[PDB]
Length: 53
Image (cartoon, rainbow, N blue to C red):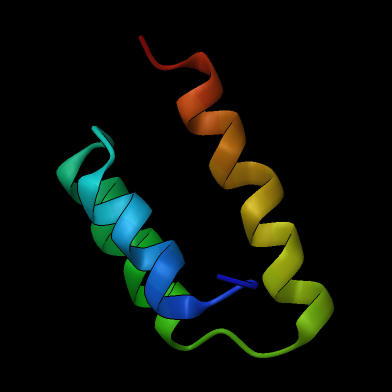
């Protein structure tokens, strides 16, 4: 997968993120606009799991 929305959402829904956090990341991810903006989303996403257990 090369920066696929379907591939990303799958990681969030599967991730152990807060029910409210996931819903937010998935809600915004669906209405994501801009290649550069979409990339930044991943930068923070990984940061979440990076800290997770």
